[PDB]
Length: 154
Length: 154
Length: 154
Ligand SMILES: CC(=O)N[C@@H]1[C@@H](O)[C@@H](O)[C@@H](CO)O[C@H]1O
Ligand SMILES: CC(=O)N[C@@H]1[C@@H](O)[C@@H](O)[C@@H](CO)O[C@H]1O
Ligand SMILES: CC(=O)N[C@@H]1[C@@H](O)[C@@H](O)[C@@H](CO)O[C@H]1O
Ligand SMILES: [Ca+2]
Ligand SMILES: [Ca+2]
Ligand SMILES: [Ca+2]
Ligand SMILES: [Ca+2]
Ligand SMILES: [Ca+2]
Ligand SMILES: [Ca+2]
Ligand SMILES: [Ca+2]
Ligand SMILES: [Ca+2]
Ligand SMILES: [Ca+2]
Ligand SMILES: [Cl-]
Ligand SMILES: [Cl-]
Ligand SMILES: [Cl-]
Ligand code: NA
Image 1 (cartoon, rainbow over the protein chains, first blue to last red):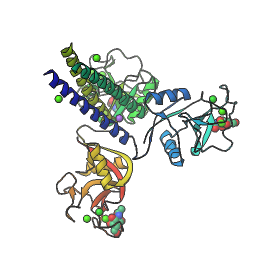
Image 2: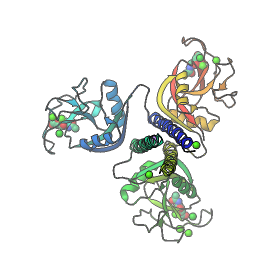
Image 3: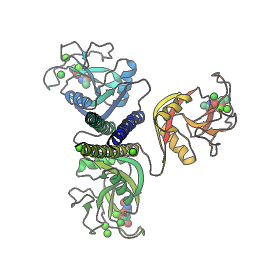
Image 4: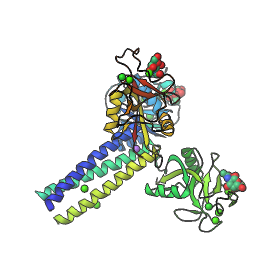
C-alpha cells in the first residue's frame, strides 16, 4: 500500500501541475494575451518606480519595456494613463539602459526630452522614464508616481 | 528509496503551492487590486440577497461592505449598477449590522431612507441595503434582485 | 514516520485541489460567468478557424456556439468584433453542424446567407460561420481570420 499510495500521489501531483498550467493559460487568454506576443498587465495604480519594480518582480514579471513601435503602442493601450517603463539612466547619467540590462535599441522620446530636469522639486534630476501623450517618452523623477505595468514573456 | 521519493514530492507540492499563490496574486493585480486596499469583484449578475451571500461565501469572500467613503466609491465603480451591500437590519429592525458582525460605523443613506418600506407588497419591509449609481444607500427588500459584489481582504 | 508523512501529503494535495477549484471559480466569476450560464471568453485575437479550434481545445473549451438568441447576444457582447462560431458545413456542403456534433437548429443568418461564396479568392467556398456586427451570421471561408471566442460549460 505505501508504494502504491506514493505512486498515486505522484500522479495526483502531475495532474495538479497540468491543471494549474491550464489555469494560467486561460487567465492570460482572457486578459488579452496574443499568440507570439508578450503580454502587459496593470492594476492601474500609480506608485514610485521602486514600488513598480518590486511589484512586477513579486509577480515574476518585469517592468514593461517597448522594443519597437508595436510594443510601445501595446503598453500605451493597457495603461491608458501615464506608466513607467523599465528604462533608466541611474547607472550613468544620460545613458539610458533597460532595467534588465543593455543599451536601448528603440526609443520614442518626446521633443526636448530627456532633459534630466530638476525643477520638479522632488530632489535630484530625472533618471526614470514614463510614456505620455501620443505614446511619446519623457524622462521623469523615479520618485514620482505613475502607472504600474508589468510584462510577461511571449 | 521511498524516503527520498517522499521528500522530493513534498518539494514539488511546495512549488505548486507557491505557483498557485502567484496565480492568485496576478489575477487580483490584473483585475485592479490596489496595494493595501480590499479587492471587490462582480460578475454583474443581479440576484436576491440570499443568492449573493451564498455566492460570495462559496468564493470564500463576503458581500461587499464599504467601511468609509473611499471604499463606497470603489464598490460603486466596480458594480456600475445597483449592488447589495453586506448590511441588513434583518435580525433587529432599525439596527443595521454587517453580515460579518457588528454595528454600522459608516453609512451614506439617501434622503428619506431608510424607510423600511412595505409598499413593494413583496412581503415585509426592507431589511437589506443597496447602492445607486449616485453612491447613496437605500434600504430595499432582501428578496429583490441586485448586483452581486464580493470582497476579499486587502 | 513514513505513514504519517504520506497522510499529511494526501492532506496537502487535497487542500491544493480545493484552492485551485476556488481560483477557477473566482476567475470565471470575475470574468462575468452568470449562474447557470455557459461563459464566453476571448483574447480579441483574429485567426483562421483551425487556429481558433486548436486554441479553445487547448483551454479545454470549444469554439463559441449560440444555442439561442440570448447566447447569441452574449457572444456578440464578448466578441465586440466579428468572431468565428463553432458551426460549419465542411463535412457535407449545405448541412451546417456544430463542431461538437449534431445538425444546426437555432440560427440567425443575415439576409441572403449562407451562400457558400467563392469570390473571396481564398480557395473553395465558405464552410465556416462568423457572427458580425448586429449579431447576424454569415458563412465565411475557414481560412479567413476572425476573433477567437471560446465557451466553457454552465
Ligand atoms: C510630465 C512631463 O512631461 N514632465 C516634464 C519634465 O520631465 C521636464 O522635462 C519639464 C521641463 O521643464 O517639462 C515637463 O513637462
Ligand atoms: C430604489 C429605491 O430607492 N427604492 C425605494 C424603496 O426602497 C422605498 O423606500 C420607496 C418608498 O415608498 O421609495 C423607493 O424609491
Ligand atoms: C462579411 C460578409 O458578409 N461577407 C460576405 C461573403 O461571405 C459572401 O456572402 C459575399 C457574397 O457577395 O458577400 C459578403 O458580404
Ligand atoms: Ca484520485
Ligand atoms: Ca537622468
Ligand atoms: Ca523630462
Ligand atoms: Ca425588518
Ligand atoms: Ca428594515
Ligand atoms: Ca427604502
Ligand atoms: Ca503543512
Ligand atoms: Ca459551404
Ligand atoms: Ca457568405
Ligand atoms: Cl530620478
Ligand atoms: Cl426584507
Ligand atoms: Cl471554407
Ligand atoms: Na484570473
